[PDB]
Image (cartoon, rainbow, N blue to C red; front, side):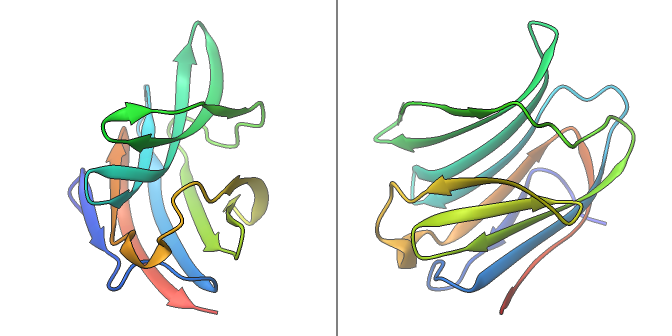
Length: 138
């Protein structure tokens, strides 16, 4: 049981083989979820499930640099369901973040921010009950 928005420090940033696991339940009438891997004010990796973008469900991924969003990467696959418990796993790999939801691979996001060891916070926000947020080295 955690308060949202929640900040998970990532000491010394991220590194390949670091696995971040987020457990929570989507609220009933959810509109959005966001994970923001931050390098100071920059957002190295924004992972943003949108439950009603012109009556479609889509996950938007992006990077924010000097307060400007870049070019979005969008996937059709949408494994979240309002009202239901989920698990998000983000595994840092040498070239990308690799995301699985409920043990199924979902997407990869190539590293735009290169200074992995400065991506030192994860913000978790949106329309969820957040149960836990943690990391481990695999």
